[PDB]
Image (spheres, coloured by chain):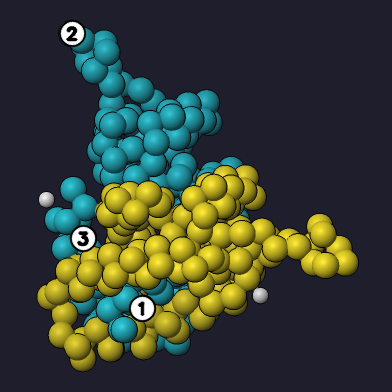
Chain colours: A yellow, B cyan
């Protein structure tokens, strides 16, 4: 039925976008996950626990990505002044610059794939799947 | 912009559905990937190479899932009569029975998440994102 095919198509779209994004972001020395870590920290410091839960990846995966971004000088580990173990991952100026480039790549790709859709069509689909997202997130956790 | 948010929302939906599906399929002793292997072989034998490429997972991931399903008696490795190394993964009767149960779980979940959408709305969204899928697959590979 249709409700099943919408979710199944959403899944296939994600897999294909994941493959292509890892490919295009590769030129910025980033993996798709690395880019997500930058997107997440672009608007404020994030705990490593949040990163893992928000993007449904393992803790080691996040540790791996954070260490890499840190070595690359795109993020820094900030510790509380009184409790140095309270860690937050903060994006650096360089990190923001790279993130913005990642965004332009993401933007370009998005325009290509949604090419057969008009502005209004894009609008209709967006407003509706946002309902789906709201529900699954209420259900999943 | 909107074209960016459609792909980003599609991604979040997929992550949330992945988490919930692994949870619900867990009762059938299956992981989300295991279920995909069953879905893929439900309509005909598939090469392990195809499974890995179609669902964008590593070769070891597929090997792991196939061995598990094989132990569970849900799939079998069929070899060519003249070249025993030519392998195809064929679903078993038991595998089909389990797959069908997985489908009902998937179906139930899909109805819940798309609950705020009417039949027509589901239709509109489906016909449009199918265009997106067609393009990304043309682009990604
Ligand atoms: Ca809840
Ligand atoms: Ca091509």
Tell me which chain the residue with mark 1 is part of.
B
- Give the residue at x 39% y 26%: B76
Q: Which residue is mark 1?
A: B5
Question: Can you name the residue that lies furthest to the right here?
Answer: A82
Q: Position of residue B47 (x, y in %)?
A: 27, 30
CA–CA distance between discs 3 and 2? 39 Å
CA–CA distance between discs 2 and 1? 52 Å
Tell me which chain the residue with mark 2 is part of.
B
Q: Relative to residue B71, is residue B110 drawn left or right?
A: left
Q: Position of residue A79 (x, y in %)?
A: 75, 62
Marks 3, 2 in one chain: yes
- Give the residue at x 47% y 63%: A95
CA–CA distance between discs 3 and 1? 16 Å
Q: Secondary structure at mark 3?
A: helix
Q: Secondary structure at mark 2?
A: loop
Q: Relative to residue B68, is residue A59 drawn left or right?
A: right
Marks 3, 1 in one chain: yes
Q: Which residue is mark 3?
A: B136
Question: Can you name the residue that lies furthest to the top here?
Answer: B82
Nearer the observer, B98 or A55: A55
Nearer the observer, A48 or B57: A48
The image quadrant where one finds the N terminus of chain B is: bottom left
Q: Which residue is mark 2?
A: B82
Report which quarter residue B94 is drawn in.
top left
- Give the residue at x 50% y 58%: A74
Q: Of callouts 2 and 1, which one flags the residue occurring earlier in the amino acid sequence?
A: 1
Mark 2 or 1: the one toward you: 1
Q: Is residue B130 above or below residue B102?
A: below
């Amino acid at each position: 039925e249709n409700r099943i095919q919408i979710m199944s198509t959403i899944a296939k779209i994600y897999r294909a976008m994941s493959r292509e994004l890892n490919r295009r972001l590769g030129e910025l020395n980033l993996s798709y996950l690395d880019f997500l870590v930058l997107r997440a920290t672009s608007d404020g410091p994030k705990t490593m626990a949040y990163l893992a839960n928000r993007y449904f990846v393992t803790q080691s995966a996040i540790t791996a990505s954070v260490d890499k971004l840190e070595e690359m000088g795109l993020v820094v580990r900030v510790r509380d002044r009184e409790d140095r173990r309270k860690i937050l991952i903060e994006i650096t100026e360089k990190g923001l610059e790279t993130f913005n480039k990642g965004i332009e790549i993401y933007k370009k790709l998005a325009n290509e794939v949604t090419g057969d859709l008009s502005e209004d069509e894009v609008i209709l689909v967006l407003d509706k799947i946002s309902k789906i997202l709201k529900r699954i997130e209420e259900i999943s956790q």
